[PDB]
Amino acid sequence: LHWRAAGAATVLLVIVLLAGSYLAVLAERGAPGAQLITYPRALWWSVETATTVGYGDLYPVTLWGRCVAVVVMVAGITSFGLVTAALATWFVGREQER
Amino acid sequence: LHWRAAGAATVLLVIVLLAGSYLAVLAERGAPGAQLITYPRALWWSVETATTVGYGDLYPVTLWGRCVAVVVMVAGITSFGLVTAALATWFVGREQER
Amino acid sequence: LHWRAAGAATVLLVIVLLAGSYLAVLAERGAPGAQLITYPRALWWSVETATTVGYGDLYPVTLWGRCVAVVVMVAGITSFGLVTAALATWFVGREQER
Amino acid sequence: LHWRAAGAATVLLVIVLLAGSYLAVLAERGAPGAQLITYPRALWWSVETATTVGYGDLYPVTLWGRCVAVVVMVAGITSFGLVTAALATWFVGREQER
Ligand SMILES: [K+]
Ligand SMILES: [K+]
Ligand SMILES: [K+]
Ligand SMILES: [K+]
């Protein structure tokens, strides 16, 4: 159904994390004012970025790594909005009945 | 109806807060650079984390407590998206009439 | 229609801001580590809190003002989710036709 | 369809960024405690503000630039909520069939 598209986000996002998580630590690590130096840092970062929390304990300073960011942000933001869209039609699905 | 699923989130989330709120202060408190040392701190944290605000005045540094985080984040994020899904079908419910 | 409920949030939220904006600066201002000392500070705060951005340049440290927070957070979070619910049925409204 | 309204946000938001991105660096740059001094800074800012992450590495201190903020915030917040509304009716569109 549409939950095959919902779990599709999950699967697809955990990738974007590991993807940009690693993809990012590289484009960052080594440049001035670097913070995303370790892999597990850039790991926690993505989690905190993809959920739009951003305590600001870690972030990119590289005009390149900052792209990884924008991809990890929209990535997370969209995924959830799509699990919200699933619960939406699911609530309308049981009202299209009753 | 679907509002029994909406209030179901509320109930269910206040738990995840108290849960991870307390569950977290433990896995954190005592480790280097720990900030989530008090219970009422780790309490305010969860509120600020589950709503994705994250001013960054408090956060986990423990690869363990950071899990509590991810659970408290998705927890809040989902819950609201589900109250958004309720208002969604409710607005469609009164349009399925008129 | 349901846009009378959408604009209803707007109206209703600008209140919660001014409300908690002012209501908060009071419960905060004067206590140790206070930051929300000015009215226009506590003003900008609410905007930054109700949209879940929280750069963390301002926040409450008072177990009381922190309540104002939780009310200003959910306030903003809900309001938007309800403008999202309006665009949702509006897109379904034009598909219930075509 | 309603995806012509979805891509309409995208187009329309990238503007609000460049718009406020630039529009902001001006109203800010030069005032005390200014941080949004460079164009590419105020650029990264908007991305981080329109997605409600706000690590707090950059933000406005000018009662004017802070307006640019509120416009960039709602701008992003709304846009996504409208892509969420598209996925919402799209999931209901394939359930209105099956
Ligand atoms: K933040
Ligand atoms: K922050
Ligand atoms: K957020
Ligand atoms: K945030």
Image: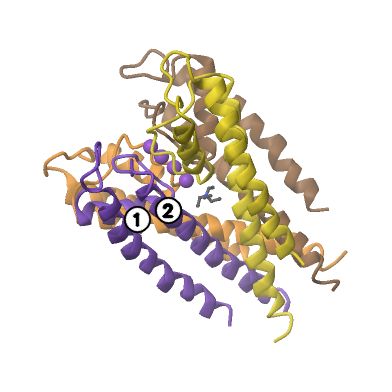
Chain colours: A yellow, B purple, C orange, D brown
- Residue at x 72% of width, y 55% of height: D86
Task: Say whether residue B9 is left or right of residue A65.
Answer: left
Q: Of the residues shown, which amino acid type is indicated by label 2?
A: Thr
Evaluate whether residue B94 shows in this view: no
Query: Which residue is pictured at 41% across the width and 58% down the height?
Result: C74
Q: What residue is disc 2 on?
A: B51
Q: Nearer the viewer, residue D37 or C11?
A: D37
Q: Quadrant of the N terminus of chain C?
A: bottom right
Q: Position of residue D60 (x, y in %)?
A: 40, 27
Q: Mark 2: which secondary structure?
A: loop
Q: Position of residue D25 (x, y in %)?
A: 48, 19
Q: Quadrant of the C terminus of chain C?
A: bottom right
Instruction: Give the labeled residue for mark 1.
Output: B47
Q: Residue at x 44, y 27 (%)?
A: D65
Provide residue A50's location: percent of width, then percent of height: 54, 43
Q: Nearer the viewer, residue C66 or A80?
A: A80
Residue D58, placed above or below residue B37: above
Q: Amino acid at mark 1?
A: Val
Mark 2 to mark 1 CA distance (whole Å): 6 Å
Q: Residue furthest right?
A: C98
Q: Is residue D9 left or right of residue A34?
A: right
**Mark 1 belongs to chain:** B
Given the current orientation, which residue lies at the most extreme bottom position? Answer: A98
The secondary structure type at the circle numbered 1 is helix
Please tell me how crowded label 1 is: few (under 14), some (14-19), or many (20+) other residues with Cα within 10 Å: many
Please state if A12 lies on the left or on the right of C44 as rendered: right
Q: Quadrant of residue B82?
A: bottom right
Q: Nearer the viewer, residue A21 or C73?
A: A21
Q: Find out whether the residues at labels 2 and 1 contact each other: C-beta distance under 8 Å.
A: yes
Q: Name which residue lies at 60% across and 29% down.
A: A23
